[PDB]
Structure formats: structure tokens, C-alpha cells
Amino acid sequence: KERTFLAVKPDGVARGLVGEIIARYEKKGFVLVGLKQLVPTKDLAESHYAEHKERPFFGGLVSFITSGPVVAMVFEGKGVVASARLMIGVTNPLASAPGSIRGDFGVDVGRNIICGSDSVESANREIALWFKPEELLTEVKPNPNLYE
Amino acid sequence: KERTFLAVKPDGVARGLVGEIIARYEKKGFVLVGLKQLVPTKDLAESHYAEHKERPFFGGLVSFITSGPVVAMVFEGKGVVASARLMIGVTNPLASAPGSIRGDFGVDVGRNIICGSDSVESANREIALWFKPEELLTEVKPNPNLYE
Amino acid sequence: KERTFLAVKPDGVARGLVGEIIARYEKKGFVLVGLKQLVPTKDLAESHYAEHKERPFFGGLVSFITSGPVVAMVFEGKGVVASARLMIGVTNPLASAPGSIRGDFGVDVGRNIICGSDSVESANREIALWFKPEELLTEVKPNPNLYE
Amino acid sequence: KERTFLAVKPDGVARGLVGEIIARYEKKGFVLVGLKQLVPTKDLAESHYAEHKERPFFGGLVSFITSGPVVAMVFEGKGVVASARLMIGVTNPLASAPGSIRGDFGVDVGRNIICGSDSVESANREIALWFKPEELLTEVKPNPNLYE
Amino acid sequence: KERTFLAVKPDGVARGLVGEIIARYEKKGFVLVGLKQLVPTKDLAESHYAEHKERPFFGGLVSFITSGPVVAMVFEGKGVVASARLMIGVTNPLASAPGSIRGDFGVDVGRNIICGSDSVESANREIALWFKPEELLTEVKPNPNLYE
Amino acid sequence: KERTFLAVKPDGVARGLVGEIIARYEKKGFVLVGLKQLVPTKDLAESHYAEHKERPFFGGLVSFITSGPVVAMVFEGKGVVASARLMIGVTNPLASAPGSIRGDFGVDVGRNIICGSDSVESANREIALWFKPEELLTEVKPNPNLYE
């Protein structure tokens, strides 16, 4: 099945939002196949954010995410990359709908709590970045009531 | 006042979602005028799904809903048929917004937890299908703070 | 497995507490094997309350419970009769602990929201009172993660 | 920082929705810089609703809001006027999305629970209407994890 | 009916716990007859804490409570003074049960979030301290489903 | 500050209870200083359960915990070892109070969802068992509103 990578960033961890966030994806029915808390390395942060490398805000992205603990997760399930994004909301928390994570909890583009993969393609890249293969679940059993 | 019919299907019952679902419509202010759990008969299931009778997925619809317990409800209140639908989300749970029932809990079109009437017209039909007149509340008292 | 009978009384129904209550027993892992809303008959109410027949408050018990809709439920699971009672709290809602149903929601002995069976013995009696055998689930499947 | 004025009207207070509403804006990260419960004066109600003065429904607006207690609040934070509106929903609760306040709790345009300022301009006016300067917090400290 | 005084102290306000706390007493069925946020005066703080005047920790109590905003409330209902205390927990949050306010949210005796009146006698005193008679609701209407 | 070790066992993970559990300790104010999901090794399981080595149920304990994924956590804060235990409940979920984790969610001694350290002494041992020193947070910053 599809897998995505989500990190709740230092601001989400510091605000005590980790469990609330995991519980939202668990209720949806996605399965947790990798999880750890870590303080990202500058090397890791720069690779993760490589797409924004030419833009002046790249260095801020890199400073913040290495500024404290991150909890890195990967979830598995049908259509999880796009669904996970729908559940986060949009870039600007102020513009994100009530009921989404950033819509419910966030106020600033610079402190928007959580990030998730763009695409199936960048998810594959990001998972291999943040996780070793031995840190990820091999045999996954979803609730039998979830999939036809 | 308007009435609609909602069934939480075998997958919603099995996942322990019944109370969560009723509590959403109670908080909104709709009044429960009929409620029961039952394992639908094939005769009942086929009439309920008669609209999809010509399509090949008709038989799957009929197999699943008779496969386990269903909790059948009817709610009363202004604009309840459309409102109830807004609160469920859309056919594809993956595409349903955060904050809706299928948006919050579901992943597969084939396991989308709950169904509700299309229209005032099919609600009237579906209620008479699933419920006897003596199983429905006659005198309804909504919260006095709900309606001008 | 053990079964118990719980009714959320007219005051709980009228206050929109039905879903909240069912969701508590679903989360605990007990399985719903019977459910319906009805306005109790005086004959039914008097049999249900037969134990208090000699006491002067018997008639009040009987008046209130027939005064509006009741949602009658039976749940199945290990030790459900005593557990269900632990989750309700004690007779006086004011004295019931935070976290219990009556502790969280109720204020008056006369409006204490829900009743549940005393014992396995009176549960058996009360279930046969309120429910026909064909209204109760025969084959029960609990979450496989609940029981060793 | 921006400030807005929100009142939960008599119907929201009477339905026990005050805490739920405040908790939504607290979780978002907006800071409470003024709060009180009062039964609005006719003079206050007419000024507050001055914009609808020419329309026939003006007098109903004025009757209802002075009909019971109101809890008047002002919140501070980036983009709070528009954000607060996004979180309330739209005029018609039936049409308001799941996850919004009116979408979750309300049914009637005439009983839509809460009102919030239109604009930064009318917020400034409404705050000075309902609150004395000494009733508002001067030094505000938001969670340090909220703003970049 | 009985009335009690509760203040959520600067630590509860700063942690965004105000709405959660009010919502607990609203769900229980107690009625809010007074509410405001204020930064307590030293004169007010010393009178409020007069009982601990001889003990060395008196001055700390007085320093903290005047250190930031407090939201002062009074609730009405049967047995509210003792019930409100049951719902808060005990002095030491570490020892307070799960399901109580201090049991759920607090860790330190010095930061225990909320205080409520000791007795009907000190409630009467504390209400007259913190509130003017014109700031309190005169005609109270509780949910009709609460009291027999 | 004190640290404790908690594991949500395979039954808690499989039931989608991970986020709910973390969110309870985050709300209390304890700080997450280590977190990962893993499928325990038999060597690890036997050391963890060494205290029950002579009893016949030792092998069952060891079979179950290595039977699926576990999410291993360590939390930091004043009095966290005893507090964490208070929040879990007692051995028998049926006997655990409403409001505790096992009281809210569990039914069987053999499937009681989560375990936490006995004492400060066994916490120290268990943390060194399950975690490498580099997997644990060194500089911890609790909410400034938590500790006097």
C-alpha cells in the first residue's frame, strides 16, 4: 500500500500537539509503520528542504527544524499522500479550514506545526532520508473493516 | 418538521463509531425520532438499493449491508436531509473534508461507514421501508433555543 | 459472554447525551447486541421497577420513565454488569466521581440520566423484559485485540 | 496585534456552548484580552446592530440579544478578524461546513449562536462599544511557539 | 439555589485552559451567573487569601495571582460548592485522580490551575469580594431536564 | 527531573490508541524525551519482564509483547513515575476507574493496553534497556507555567 512521511515540527512538539495529530491519522484508519523523535541534523534538514534551496527562506526552514525535537512518522494506506495533505490544510494556517490540523491549531506560515510529503515520489525520497529500512514495519495489518 | 434516514453500516458498527456519529447529529440539534439495530434482510437491502439495481455493483451493496448489524436512525429538524449529507461528506472518503464523518474516519468508497437519504422524497420512502409507524416518535420537542 | 441492560432515561435523551453514552461503552470494548428507542409502557415500567414497589418513590420512578423516550441498550462483554456500573457512578450524581457518566453530566438523584442492571441475575430479567429474542444479536464478534 | 470582538448570544449561552467556543479560539492560539457576561442594554444592542437599522429584521436582532445573558469576548492575534469568521462559518448554520462552530452546532439563521466582527474597522468600533479600556489586557504574551 | 466562586489562575489562563474548564461545569449542568477576566489587585488578592495570612506561603499566593490575568467565575446549582471541589481534585495535582481538572492538567501544588470556594460560607464572602451585585445574573433558568 | 518508561503494547497500537495515550501525558504537562515504534526482540522482552521470570505467565508476557509493534516512550517531569501509574489505572482494566487509560479502554488483564515503570529504580533500568542515550533528549524545556 502507499506510504507518506509527516514530521511534526519543533513548534508542534513544544505546544503538546503530537498525540492529537497521531490520533487524527489513526482514527482515519492509516497505519503507523514508522515513528521516532529526534533533533534533526543540519545535513538532514538541508536534504529534506533541497527543493527550496535557491530561495532566500531556505535557511530559515533549515534553522527552525534543527532548533528542537521533531517527531518523524510514516503512515500507510490507500491514497495517504493526498489525504494526509487534505487533513493538514494549506500553507497559511489562517486560511486553512476549521477541522484541518493547521486550520484548528496554527496561526503563522512560519509556525505551521506539521509537514507532509508532496507526492508519492517525494514521499519515497523523504522516508529513505529520515528512516532506515529496519525502522519501518514490514507486515502491515489494517483494520479489516477499512478496505473492501 | 423534515425527517431523514441514516444507517451506520456494518463497517461503522464494527469499528465502534455508532455513538460518535449519533453525538454529532445530537450536538447539531436534530432530534432522534427513531432508532434500532438490526441485521438487514436481503429483501429490505434490495428495496433500499433499488436505484442502483441495473448497475453491476448493486449486488455488492446488497451483500455488505446484510453482512452484519446496521444501526438505523431517523432524525428530525429543519433542512435535515441536506444538512445530514453535508455532515457525512462525499462518496469518496479520501476526498471528504476534515470535519465530516467520512472525511474523519473513512478511507474506501466500499467502506464509507454511513449512508443518508438523497432527498426529502427518498427519505420518506426509506423511513417507511426500515421503520414501522409505531417505532417513530410522534410528539417531538426540540431544544427551545434552536429555532426562532 | 455476560450481558447487561442499560437505559438512558428521558432526561438523558432530552439533553442530547445518547451518543456520548454509547461511545463510552464502545471505546471500552463492549459490544452492542441490542438497541432501540421507545416510550416505555406503564406495564413495562412497573415490572422494571418492581424491586421498589413497596416504597413511596415507586410511582415517581414509574411516572418519569414513561414520560418521554428512552433508549434501551444491551451490551456484551467480560464483566460488563459491574463495569457498566463503575462507569455510570453512584446514585447521587453530585457524589459520583469526575470521569463517570453521572459524575460528568448529572446533578439530581431524580435526574441521573442512565440506569444499568444491578446483577447478572437482574440483567437477565431486564433484557427479557425490554427486548424480544429476535431483537438481540446472536453471533458476536468483539475486537480481536480485546481478549487474551 | 489585531483584535476582534465575538459575542456568544443568548442561545449559545443557554445551550451550554460557551466553554466549547472559547476553547476553539484558545487552541488556535488567539489570546483573550477581554471577557465578561452581561445582559445587553437596548441602547447597546441598537448601536451594535446599527448597520441593519433600516431593515425590518433590525428589531428582532435587538429583541433577542437583550433577551438573556451574552458572553462578550475580545481575542488578539494575527489575522484574527477574518480567521474568527472562518471558524464561525456562514450566516446560515445549515450551510456552514462541518468543523465550524455554526456548522457543528446550529440550525437556524435566527439562532446562530455567535457573532464576530465584520472587519478590522467594525471590530474597533464594537470593542469600544462593549468594553471599557480598563477591562482589556494591555500587555499580551502569546505562546512563543506561535509566531515566527 | 447555591452558588460558588471559581478562579482559573494565571497559569491556567496562560496554558489555554479556560474554555475546557468552563465546558466541564456547563456539561455538569451548573449555570454561569457571573464571569470576567481581570488582573487581580494586591488588595483583592490579600483579602481573598486572608485565611493563610499567618503562614509564610501567604506572600507567594499573593504574588502569583496578581502576576497575570485571572478569569473569575461564579456558578449556580444544587450542591455546587462541594461538587465543584470534587471536579477540581485535591491540593496536589500529582495526587488528583484522572478525570479531575488538576488530575488531568496539573503537576505542581504551586501551579494547580484553578481554585474554588471551600464552603457555602466562604463562597458567599468570595463572590461579594470579586463581583459587584450588578455583575451577577438575577433570574436563572437551568435546563428543565436537570432537576426533579 | 524524574523520568519514566511507558510502552503501549501490541493491543493498544493495533486498536489505534497511541495518539490518545500520548495526548493524555502531554496535557498533564510531562515532556516526551524519547519515542519510537519497534517490534521487541525476545532478548529485550525477557529482560524487561525479568521480575516475573519464575512465574508460569512469564512466557505469555514475552510472547505477546514480541507479537507485534510496540511504541516505547519516556516522559520527564516531577513525580512522573507514580503519576503515570495513577493515569494508567490498576492491573485489572475492569476494576480501573473511569478516566484512567485502562479504565476507559480496556477489558482484560491480558490485553491492558499499556505498561509503565514500577519505580524510579526500575524506570532507570527500563529506559537503559529500550533506549540508547543518543535517542533521549538532553536539554528539556517544560511549559514555564507548569512549575513554581
Image (cartoon, coloured by chain):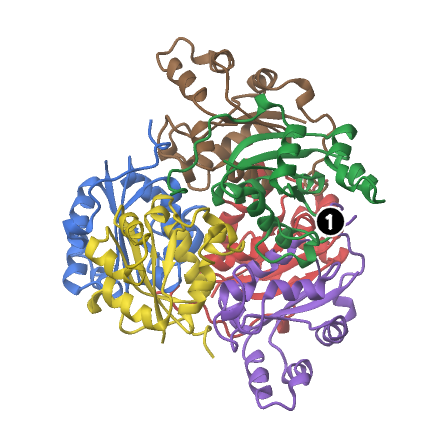
Chain colours: A red, B blue, C yellow, D brown, E green, F purple
Tell me if residue C121 comes above or below residue D30 in the rendering: below
Mark 1, residues whose alpha carbon is within 10 Å: few (<14), some, or many (≥20)? Answer: many
Residue D115, how many percent across, how many down?
48, 26
In depth, the one of B110 and D119 nearer the eye is: D119
In depth, the one of E85 and D99 nearer the eye is: E85
Q: Write the residue at 46% across / 61% down.
A: C87
Tell me if residue F122 comes above or below residue B12 in the rendering: below
Q: Is F80 displayed left or right of B34 in the figure?
A: right
Instruction: Residue type at mark 1: give it.
Output: Leu
Q: Chain of mark 1?
A: F
Q: What is the residue that sits farthest to the right in this orientation?
A: E56
In depth, the one of E144 and F27 nearer the eye is: E144
Looking at the rendered structure, the secondary structure element under dot 1 is loop
Residue C78, how many percent across, how many down?
42, 74
Residue F108, how many percent across, how many down?
49, 75
State whether residue F78 appears in this view: yes
State whether residue B49 appears in this view: no
Give the position of the C terminus of chain A as an image quadrant.
bottom left
Residue D65 lies in quadrant: top left
Residue B44 lies in quadrant: bottom left
In depth, the one of B38 and C114 nearer the eye is: C114
Residue C130 lies in quadrant: bottom left
Q: In this figure, what is the number of numbered marks?
A: 1
Q: Write the residue at 65% across / 88% down.
A: F53
Tell me if residue A110 comes above or below residue B108 in the rendering: above
Tell me if residue C38 comes above or below residue A106 in the rendering: below
Residue B139, how many percent across, how many down?
22, 40
Q: Residue at label 1?
A: F146
